[PDB]
Amino acid sequence: PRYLKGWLEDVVQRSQRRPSVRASRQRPIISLKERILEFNKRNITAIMAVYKRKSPSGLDVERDPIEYAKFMERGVVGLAILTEEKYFNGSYEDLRKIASSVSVPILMWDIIVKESQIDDAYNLGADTVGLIVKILTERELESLLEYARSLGMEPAIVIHDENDLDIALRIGARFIIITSHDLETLEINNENQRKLISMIPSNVVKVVASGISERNEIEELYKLGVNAFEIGTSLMRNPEKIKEFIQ
Ligand SMILES: Clc1cc(Cl)c2[nH]nnc2c1
Ligand code: NA
């Protein structure tokens, strides 16, 4: 990984030491990217709902992961499940349960720093993983992107600024998540969102993560050509809002 400090450095070391899990997936991979494109062609809002019990910014809720997944399955394009242990209180067991219990594609949401974590995603039933440009050297991104592809996944490349986007497009990202979250500070900053979205070619599937909590914000971003919307905290606090987001 890159040289990092603070909580990210902690999670990066945690990830490097993380033992590979015993698991066996129960259906072939369903491309999350391609399901988003099918939602787009059908003119149906594509929401990727996030399951997380906590966040380093202060989320703290308890909700049964299967019930939440079953509830969301009816309306989402897919689910992102936290498996990061210390800051998000997630685990591989949440993914194993959800990915075996719902039919929609699943992104494993964690800090990936090594191939065996992508193995873990695959064996646990996830359909794809995110790789984070701020965390990974360009060489590690290239390598892990190639490795995910070799398993049948198209990973989401997570970018926050123009420097990250430069990298993601150079390595040939086909699926990008544009986050307003500064992973260091934890603050949501939207200053550069409009510019970043507009720099991504039309045939790259783009997803926005930004503390979204209102249908209006989705409508605004969709006008810019955004394909899908990752929504975590507002749905963890009130899952019933999925209806405002997809109606
Ligand atoms: Cl896997 C992953 C990692 C990060 Cl930092 C993300 N930020 N927004 N969506 C994400 C998915
Ligand atoms: Na560095």
Image (cartoon, rainbow, N blue to C red):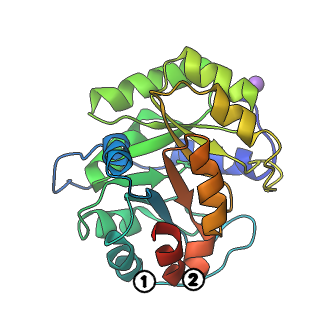
Q: Is residue 3 above or below residue 246?
A: above
Q: Is residue 229 above or below residue 90?
A: above
Where is the N terminus found, in terms of image quarters?
top right
Where is the C terminus found, in terms of image quarters?
bottom left
Q: Amino acid at mark 1?
A: Asp
Q: Secondary structure at mark 2?
A: loop
Residue 22: quarter of image? bottom left
Give ligand 2's quarter of the image. Answer: top right
245 to the left or right of 66:
right
Could you tell which of marks 2 and 1 lies nearer the N-terminus?
A: 1
Marking on residue 221: none
Residue identified by numbered label 1? 64
> Disc 1 beta carbon < 8 A from ligand 1?
no
Residue identified by numbered label 2? 238
**Residue sitting at x 49%, y 19%:** 172
**Residue sitting at x 37%, y 63%:** 95
